[PDB]
Amino acid sequence: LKELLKRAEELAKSPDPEDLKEAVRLAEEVVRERPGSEAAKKALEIIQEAAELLKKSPDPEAIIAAARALLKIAATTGDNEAAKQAIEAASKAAQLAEQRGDDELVCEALALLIAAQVLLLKQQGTSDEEVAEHVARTISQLVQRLKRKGASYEVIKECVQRIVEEIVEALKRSGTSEDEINEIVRRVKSEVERTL
Ligand SMILES: [Ca+2]
């Protein structure tokens, strides 16, 4: 346990994305094994440290790993700054993926971006009706744009599935009850159906 924690702290000092991704995995393991311990709190500090270096990489896959880790911290702790950092990283990744016309990679980044947006909206007190409207408009606009662009059916389906999955996961990790999540998804589905 403490061994995993020490090695994660070491790997988090290396700007190499392979070392940083491993640092995140080791620390996230500590969190999963000792959820509310002091080692878990130490692990979250290491994850945030490693993620801030990963986000500075020029590689979209590395930046996405940073956004995913920052989003997990945000949901786990209710840290608004963590959520804003996840948005920053996901946005950077989305633009680099767009640059190379990789819609699949764009959607990976957007799913994390939208999930972080939902988290912040909830942390700031926005209503579930407004959250659902934000998500529905974003999905509807994205689906229509990818259709115009020529993205395949499976790419678009995966895009939407990933967005919804990341939102649900982030809301669950942040303590949102399953009753509230289901109601939010219901609203989103109703609006997307009308639009689409
Ligand atoms: Ca996840």
Image (tube, helix red, strand yellow):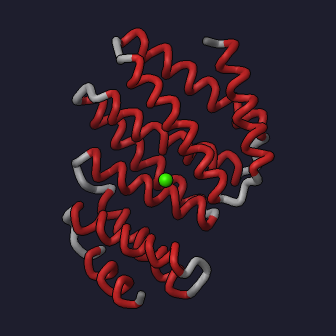
In the figure, residue 182 lies in which quadrant?
Answer: top right
In the figure, residue 23 lies in which quadrant?
Answer: bottom left
Q: Nearer the viewer, residue 82 or 158?
A: 158
State whether residue 132 is above or below residue 72.
Answer: above
Q: In the rendering, at what x and y percent does residue 137 appear?
A: 61, 23
Q: Which residue is painted at 30% across and 74% down in the image?
A: 12
Q: In the rendering, at what x and y percent does residue 175 appear?
A: 71, 60
In the rendered view of the protein, which quadrant contains the N terminus?
Answer: bottom left
State whether residue 127 is above or below residue 33.
Answer: above
Q: Nearer the viewer, residue 158 or 117?
A: 158
Q: Which residue is painted at 59% across and 52% down in the image?
A: 170
Q: In the rendering, at what x and y percent does residue 24 appear?
A: 37, 68
In the rendered view of the protein, which quadrant contains the C terminus?
Answer: top right
| Residue at the extreme top of the image, as rendered | 148
Q: Which residue is painted at 36% across and 17% down in the image?
A: 152
State whether residue 94 is above or below residue 192.
Answer: below
Q: Which residue is painted at 41% across and 45% down in the image?
A: 90
Number of numbered callouts drawn: 0
Q: In the rendering, at what x and y percent does residue 160 appear?
A: 51, 29
Query: Position of 82 compared to 18: left or right?
Result: right
